[PDB]
Length: 9
Length: 236
Ligand SMILES: C[C@]12CC[C@@H]3c4ccc(O)cc4CC[C@H]3[C@@H]1CC[C@@H]2O
Image 1 (cartoon, each protein chain N blue to C red):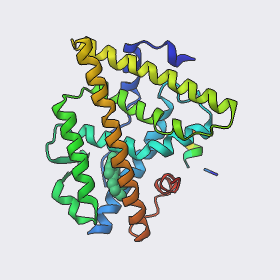
Image 2 (tube, chains in turn purple, cyan):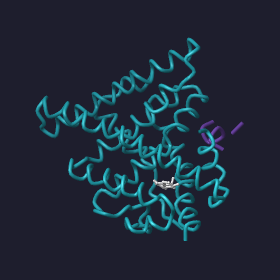
Image 3 (cartoon, each protein chain N blue to C red):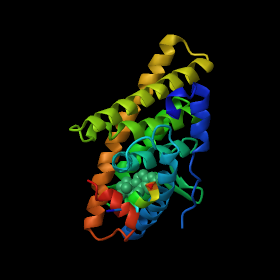
């Protein structure tokens, strides 16, 4: 799952 | 392993340059919509900031996600408390959003939390908290809040924690260093250090009450569909 996941990567 | 080599002065400097931009802001529902819209936008910038916090990118992604999920509201509170510090009795959410205590009564149960936040702001003011201390405290919060809530079943997971506690040690040395430059006795330094870390304990408290309040407001259907904020909220 993720937005957090995507902005940290 | 950049983090552990940084000196006191390099740590403080590096933290002052990771500081996020101060955002401008744009009945009970509308008050909650106002505050959560700010919070949601800052979250985007808090992620950029966390990546610039020494030792943070060294963690696994799943642990980065874990620390931010645990600490985020604590991090918005300490920042709000800090910039309100010169504004007695007022909460400076944004440069165009300076809220009175009595403006907390717009929302059920919020004036209570405003009271807690303004008392913390007064404490920081009476202590003459420095900006260099603030950035140290906020990074401690990010690093320490979820460190105890990590998967304690893996050797890798046990190394992540050890690395986090070596970095937090660094920040303690950094705080001590700052207090010595300010010309404090050894006694006065470790007294100030403890007075500050004990405040992180009230901030964790304020954050627990605010998380309860926001989940309750979400249940009233008075929180807009801010995707990142709900993402953080729903990790509890
Ligand atoms: C989380 C709440 C909305 C967002 C508020 C906010 C929003 C932005 C910010 O920088 C700090 C804070 C601290 C208090 C928070 C509130 C306490 C309860 C309410 O639900």
